[PDB]
Amino acid sequence: SNPRLTKVLDEMSKKPCVNINEIRKMIRNFQPQFIQPRNGNRPNAQPRTVDSFEWVVRIQSTVETQLLGATNTVPQQTLNLDISFTDDSTTITPASIPGSISMLDNSRHIPAIQSMIQNFKARYLGSLQDTAQLQSPQYPQLLAYLFGQLIAIKDRLDLFRPSNPLSLADALFGFTLAQNARPRYDDHRHAKACQGPLVIPAATNSDCGPCGFVQINANQGLTLPLGACLFVNPETVNDQSFQDFLWLIFATHHRMPNQMQNNWPFSLNIVSTCAAPGRQAPHAGELTDERVRLALDTGHRILLSMFNDDEETLRYYQRKGIETMFRPCCFYTEGGLLRKATRYVSMVPLNGLYYYNGATSYVVSPIHTDAHPGITAAIESFVDIMVLQAVFSFSGPKVVAAKVNASQIDAAMVFGPAVAEGDGFVYDPLRPAPPLSAFYTEFIHRPAEQRIFQMAMSQIYGSHAPLIIANVINSIHNCKTKIVNNKLRATFVRRPPGAPHLKADTAIINRFHDPELAYALGILADGIAPLDGSHEYNVLDELDYLFNGGDIRNCFGLNALNTRGLGQIVHIRPKREPGKRPRRGFYTTLDGQVHPVTQDAPLDEIYHWRDHGNLTRPYSCHILDSQGLEFADVSNGRSRGKILVVVNSPLKTCAAYQGPSFAP
Amino acid sequence: SNPRLTKVLDEMSKKPCVNINEIRKMIRNFQPQFIQPRNGNRPNAQPRTVDSFEWVVRIQSTVETQLLGATNTVPQQTLNLDISFTDDSTTITPASIPGSISMLDNSRHIPAIQSMIQNFKARYLGSLQDTAQLQSPQYPQLLAYLFGQLIAIKDRLDLFRPSNPLSLADALFGFTLAQNARPRYDDHRHAKACQGPLVIPAATNSDCGPCGFVQINANQGLTLPLGACLFVNPETVNDQSFQDFLWLIFATHHRMPNQMQNNWPFSLNIVSTCAAPGRQAPHAGELTDERVRLALDTGHRILLSMFNDDEETLRYYQRKGIETMFRPCCFYTEGGLLRKATRYVSMVPLNGLYYYNGATSYVVSPIHTDAHPGITAAIESFVDIMVLQAVFSFSGPKVVAAKVNASQIDAAMVFGPAVAEGDGFVYDPLRPAPPLSAFYTEFIHRPAEQRIFQMAMSQIYGSHAPLIIANVINSIHNCKTKIVNNKLRATFVRRPPGAPHLKADTAIINRFHDPELAYALGILADGIAPLDGSHEYNVLDELDYLFNGGDIRNCFGLNALNTRGLGQIVHIRPKREPGKRPRRGFYTTLDGQVHPVTQDAPLDEIYHWRDHGNLTRPYSCHILDSQGLEFADVSNGRSRGKILVVVNSPLKTCAAYQGPSFAPK
Amino acid sequence: RGLGQIVHIRPKREPGKRPRRGFYTTLDGQVHPVTQDAPLDEIYHWRDHGN
């Protein structure tokens, strides 16, 4: 029955959204150019240890406009797309909704191991089907997350050359570290890595490395352990690469903080027909780069085999393991609201039965072979948040304010027609800041946003979308972040103490980054026009639409002339239309400051705003409402000019501007 | 087939009653102007411990009448409301009726709990996958009641600022106490609170603050304990404020009377997936004001999540809990009993399965942060007691009198006009007094004082009406309070156990406080008409309306001149029947005497009633019967003038004089 | 003399389109607004010369 939603769904159906594969393909070979700290500049020589948690790899992107039929030269602006580079956070949470985490079927694994046991004349108890079903289900999720974390550590330590590196393994096993010193790759305030050299478990009778080992003997009882069992052919257990991979995972799991080493035990047990090779813990430098590369390759082979040869869920989990190191930064004052609310992945302890006799599918382009896995992982997350922003900002800007007299009056007290009546919330500042979860949970579950978010995600991903939708719904439904009134200043990574209060104390909780990036990527874009090419503005009507609550970002003429004209091109005067009592026209800004307009004056003397060229804050919600105003031009018919805009971003993809929208 | 009933229903439809949000909006945010003991004056400095159970914040409000034609000016009266603010009382009873208490639905606590118990649970107890055995009763009531009691403690300490203060936590726990001495607060004759310093329970293996703890891990076992289980993520259990909130709730639960403590055990116990954080047992000065406030906030969030995010019943139980220590104080010498029979909330021992992960909602102004919640709870109660008053009085005063050698079979004698046949009972005095539940129940079941109650409460509260209604009815059914021959003297909290005696040995059992407040607040009011503006009065007819079974309060034409010179205005003569027979006339007062009138004489020495000003007892039944009177006038005019009454009260609500009523036009 | 407890001012009770708030402008420029029901004595509070 809703017309607007039907129109949007029809348009989305007619113009399909860009498949994820293009976005993956267009980043596999991207060479970063800037590794400066977010705030300052790179010092002469790199430090010896990753300490300043402010570094960022900057994907520069430039936009400059021109006023056709004029001699004005607007300075070029800069779409600063920042990727956090040294900062640790957690993306694991044991809390799932029904579709959040699935159970990979053990259809092709049980028969093979059954036949193996029968062939080697091992006396087992009970048909393996029911014992598999009840004793040990099949959740290999964890072992991919650790792999992603390892790749992320490698990438981080690679980009930031710490002036005398050792190796992937020498900075990971903590050789020559004081009992209180932190690992080289992660040494700064509020890190998330256990400190000191990691300690190998004691050498027991039978060991295939850092995990237990059980061999199957002809005419001999066989009993499985309690964790996960990975049957392998004897040709592999004696391989160097396999054991090196196993050791690397073990090391990565004993470095994550102490308290998650007792909730997600890294339990595994290799089973085969060899003689227990025993653990051979590498001690001195003996894991050269080529050996580590082989280890990673064999490891990915085993992982892909465990996932029923899916390579899509595996890629998703491997990525979700990486954001723990690489995150996409915000581009607004009150940021860290969307990313902080969509990061968690529901998980279950690792257990079940596996079988690997030989690889079957040859993944051409795995994650770990990309030019820089961190960037590739971060960009996919950026896409997720972009779509989420698109769905959220479907019916307004969703403001939240801190008015002291909050109880005395209800909502819609201050926000005029601009903020859709129903999306403005307030809270008195006497109490602590509310929980963002409260607002977002109510936002997501409305039918209008649900029925569109589902379609968008399905178009982007496909058969594998439902996992992502369920997981994001869970995460947003489970977030502890508060809407703190402070500001971020957009020149840091973590909120600095003593920062000033927000603008008008009104946080806006849709924005995460400019929609021009979404347009370029070819993904769903919110109701903002794409500043792409030639435009034909008309300052009068354009300006009039602004004072009805519209976003200034949709007004090209004003932004172009913000300080080069508009003091000699347009005037503002009260409306004298009827014969009734004359009234002083007034307009209300965001903070409820009713502004009167008595004597007609040049526009620049009535309203002001900073000139960011043509990249202004999209949803700034400048003018809530205005009544009784007229706009007359005082230039001899040169207020309807044309402008040109060029956006040569380096992350443009095939579907340049073919993505859907709301206001084409 | 009841003209009065249909007329009143139509009227109430015409002018809807003000829903409670206006009352909350008005009262939420004013501080009391002055707090003093009910009888006397406050001392120079407050003592160490609240020990006199009379301190009461009061709310002045006056009436001034003004008119020309009288001899001298009329002195003003002081209609002030009081709040008990110190004395304790029980409010929790085990009885029940259909709607008295309801069980919430665990339709959004079972999915998550099952999905979190299926995975992290040793793979040798079998797969559960049934989602049908997790069906324990959901009764998360008592938690809110304890929360309310805690808020009440905080407020009572704040209002009556004692000389040497202590941290709310320190006062509540009471580390530096004596062997069996009372807590720093609530130390007086009527105080009922477990004395002595509070004792932390034990040093067991699995501790998580005051309550039990069970974990679900592979190398463990799982067995849900019997009480309530609050399944939370490992993130919050290791938090700080949450632990403090648990300690606070436990602390307030062990100060209830020992017997009531045994009845309703504190059976909460938490289950999670991480190592048990040992009990902290704060002492000396660990908890402080801001930390306590943070704990309160998180506790409120927890409780809201437990209530299926209802927040209207949550506020109800929280109010009812805070009502054990604040409550309106009656205003009539009768003894202030109408409240005592409406104060009970049914309850059952807490139980169920609860999961808590986030917020799911944000309430702009919860009760616990509104500048002295005690006052707002007390007034939220008063705004219901007044409605009950209005409904009972819908028929008549409903007196109960005492006569010697009354028939111990039936106690229903007709008293005359102004008292309908149903009401107006009688009882022998020398035997124990009646139970006062043998009248109210009979009152609120008739289909005239029922539908009115239904619609009025519906308009006041809306959807969450039934619960209140049902509950109050239950309170009436089992109330042990009894009628007594004594007075409150208007400067007491409880009857002084001496020998106060009734003026007429009778008791009017349907008046609690002056209806003027009811009119001002916009709630329903009956009978008595409002007095705020100019009025046309006809003594020659108003007085006639009086002697045929009225009450003076409606007759504001008389009180103005009661002793300002009504004497030489009107005469009463027996009767001037020009025919059958010249008989003489008489009137009967509330007592038995029937002193008669024979000749013309000034009115001032035939009735001669006490003059309060323009605020007389509304249901006093000054005259019951009178036959054969004329009320001649003795001055041309001078009995058809005007009068102006101004009443200004600080609690004027938003819609003050736009509420329903059915007082004579 | 007591106009306070005689009349209240409230923003508006429009039963339909939108609950917006109201304000008044004095001879100076300031446009201080009114949001809730409140006594008149503290919203305007003009100097009293008599009649």
Image (cartoon, coloured by chain):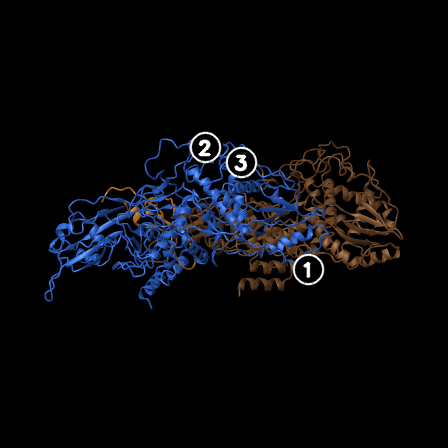
Chain colours: A brown, B blue, C orange
Taking the image as drawn, is residue A364 in sight? no
Residue B81: which numbered mark, if any? none
Q: Callout 1: 10 Å neighbours few (<14), some, many (20+)?
A: few
Tell me residue A212's x, y (percent). 81, 45
What chain does badge 1 belong to? A
C-alpha gap between disc 1 and disc 3: 54 Å
Q: Callout 3: 10 Å neighbours few (<14), some, many (20+)?
A: some
Residue B287: which numbered mark, if any? 3
Q: Amino acid at mark 1?
A: Gly
Q: Which residue bears the numbered disc 1?
A: A462
- A470, above or below C45, in the image: below
Tell me residue A635's x, y (percent). 46, 52
SS at mark 2?
Answer: loop
Farthest residue to the right: give it: A218
What chain does badge 3 belong to? B
Q: Quadrant of the N terminus of chain B?
A: bottom left
Of the two numbered discs 2 and 3 on the same chain, state the one appearing first in sequence.
2
C-alpha gap between disc 2 and disc 3: 15 Å
Q: Which residue bears the numbered disc 2?
A: B165
Tell which of C21 and B624 is nearer to you.
B624
SS at mark 1?
Answer: loop
- B160, above or below A230, in the image: above
Tag 2 and tag 1, C-beta contact below 8 Å: no
SS at mark 3?
Answer: loop
Same chain assignment for discs 2 and 3: yes
